[PDB]
Amino acid sequence: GFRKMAFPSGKVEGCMVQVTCGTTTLNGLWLDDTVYCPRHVICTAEDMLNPNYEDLLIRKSNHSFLVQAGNVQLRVIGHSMQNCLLRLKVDTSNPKTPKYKFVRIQPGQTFSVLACYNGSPSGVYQCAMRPNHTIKGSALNGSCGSVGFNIDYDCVSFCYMHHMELPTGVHAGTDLEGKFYGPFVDRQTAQAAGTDTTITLNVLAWLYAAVINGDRWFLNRFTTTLNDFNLVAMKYNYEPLTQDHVDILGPLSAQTGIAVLDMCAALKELLQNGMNGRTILGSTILEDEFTPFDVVRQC
Amino acid sequence: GFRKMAFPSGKVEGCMVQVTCGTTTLNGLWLDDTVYCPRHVICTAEDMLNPNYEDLLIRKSNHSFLVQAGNVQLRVIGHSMQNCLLRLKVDTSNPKTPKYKFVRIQPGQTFSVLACYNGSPSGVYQCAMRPNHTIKGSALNGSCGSVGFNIDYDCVSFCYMHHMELPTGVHAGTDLEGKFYGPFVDRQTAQAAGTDTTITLNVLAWLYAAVINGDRWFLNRFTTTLNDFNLVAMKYNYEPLTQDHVDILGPLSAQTGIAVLDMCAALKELLQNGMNGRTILGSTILEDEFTPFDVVRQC
């Protein structure tokens, strides 16, 4: 098979804290002398129906916030609001602060989430930002203040923070500047996600990972155009494949000697005929949570 | 629940080393002042056809083994063999040793694997020990010396270490006493693997997780005995369900208000009729890599 691996979580584990404001407690990211958490930590369940955050935050002081790093009480010496984030200045700088970056990822791109339970690391999983700008998972999977990240050598690129749980186990979130992904907001209203689609570029990359691991049964002599593939793509709830996408599949096409549009033809047949008791990389379904970058790296 | 979370890998990351003997390099486990790795590190390709481990090791000095933790080269001052493991005494105790136990797990049980390339933590995944005593994955997923573990409270329970990649593309390995799971040996030969049945207990645990998370379309009013359920289950390559398994699902049964045998009749119908394009916890297939303990822990 081909395991959907999360990044080793060690560097992010040392950064997780809990933040308590009144009766509300959630997770926060402790980097240097700042703690980052969702701004709705200052909101009770009642407050969430129509929250005036500037109105609610003026009533708070530095002592309104209880920050705890494991068994250690951190002392907050400043507070401010950056978009949908609460920024807390503390009197101690995190000695386990790794090399880090804040990045804004694109839909269809992947990252690891370290699910945390009131400051404490519980589990890690790999996921993709869905085309509808949501992250799938349970209440624990998307526990508020839990962060998404990529690790590139020694540097942690933080790209996501869990904020809201939408109906039927769907999560909405923010980057590390507090800007939401998608048309979502930090209040309890009716928020429907858009139409979720299969990440076509990702499926193709995973089919290339299949070939690299010796799985070849799905390939064919057939040839398709980009337009005729996208006619079959939309029919089965797949994302349109841009010319820019076929460029990104260059290195994987070269490594296997299989032309992108030939793999599209293979995908087309798979979409129309199914797998018929056969597996690809030990799977009965077409995986879409591996980017070309993930495949090249893990192959 | 929904997402198949691995444990936070932090405590295990600080234990990973690379061990080199001759032309072979693999992963090792550094705990206190001992380094654990597969004994076949002392073997070349030709050795692996018919390895005489006693003889191969007898003319190896302490200097024959190169061990490095990150960039620190560890001085090996002892060597011995524990079953299929090499035990290398080093001059320094691992300062990053966590509280740990070695345990042998049962087939169908779950653990996390920190996959490593030449001592460097690469990724982390959650898996189950198959009923045929194998672990599915790629070459990197099961790269020699990578360990499996659970984290219970503050304590790391190491249970598994990758040794061999089997012809089928699956992986064989030992516990941390060096005793293989299943009828496998550390020699490059033809090896009979049993049938990979579906872990029935785990599917039922997962169906309970679905109910708890408000996904209960698969439930019906039908009844069944353990005997009659197995006659259907044996036909779809599910392992027999025992009274012991029924008892294990007792707490989840009481929590959901759904009797085990009723959940069995729900499964029976799912096996016969299929899911019919519907999803359970966002999945189009039935998951068998969550234990009852995993379900309770994550819900």
Image (cartoon, coloured by chain):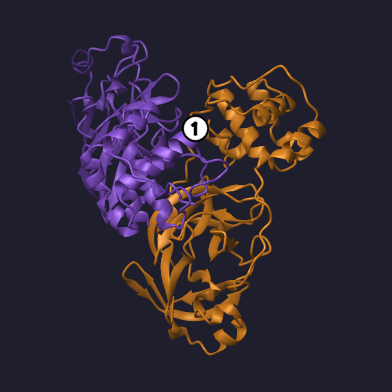
Chain colours: A purple, B orange
- For residue A110, say whether it is visible: yes
Name the residue at 28% across, 9% down. Answer: A50
Name the residue at 41% across, 69% down. Answer: B18
Q: Is residue B96 left or right of A41 when viewed as pictured? A: right
- For residue B156, say whether it is visible: no
How far across and down, in percent of the image, does residue A116 sit?
41, 36
> Quick check: B86 above or below B286?
below
Q: Is residue A262 left or right of B161 when viewed as pictured? A: left
> Quick check: B266 above or below B131?
above
Name the residue at 46% across, 58% down. Answer: A214
> Quick check: A158 above or below A215?
above
Outermost residue to the front: A222
Residue type pointed to by label 1: Phe
Of residues B176 and A14, the one nearer the viewer is: B176
Which secondary structure, mark 1? loop
Mark 1 — on which chain does it sit?
Answer: B
User: Badge 1 is on which residue?
Assistant: B2
Quarter of the rendering containing residue B179 = bottom right
